[PDB]
Amino acid sequence: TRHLKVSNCPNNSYALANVAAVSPNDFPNNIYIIIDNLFVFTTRHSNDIPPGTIGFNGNQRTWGGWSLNQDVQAKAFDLFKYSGKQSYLGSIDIDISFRAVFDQDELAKQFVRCYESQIFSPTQYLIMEFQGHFFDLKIRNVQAIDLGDIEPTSAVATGIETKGILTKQTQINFFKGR
Ligand SMILES: *[C@H]1CC(=O)N(CC)C1=O
Ligand SMILES: *[C@H]1CC(=O)N(CC)C1=O
Image (cartoon, protein in one colour):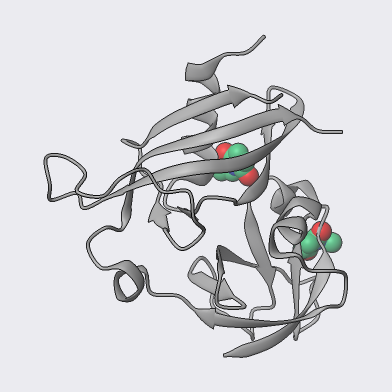
């Protein structure tokens, strides 16, 4: 369990990849970590981030309710341990809007391309680039499933407690924001 200070990470290599920028000596690269017992992100090493700090873009900070320099608690995250079999995303509904032509199929491809294997949960706020434009994505709801079942046993979830891994078979539903 690490204690890290939140810093802004606007560089597009990170800001568009929806990752938690960490120092190589705080966490290994590309693993799941959970912040403040609620927010799960995939890690990404950065040599330009002070050991003891963790970088997030504006949307991720808004989601966690973290202000700059705010101390935060981070721990390696084990999805199985957390939710057992109901660990994969069967579907995910996203509220999408232009950052401060609507193609559902293309937006979905880009989403899987950029975030496959990442964990998502309702309420999660992230930034995604699509054909030269930046968009704010808010995960509205999720449908967690056990890949072993021919159909979901659980209902569509709206709470941040339900977390699931994005796969190439996850149905992605976008909603032209407001
Ligand atoms: C966050 C992580 C990183 O290395 N950068 C570039 C300076 C960020 O924006
Ligand atoms: C966002 C979109 C994408 O494909 N990447 C890298 C694989 C991003 O960072």
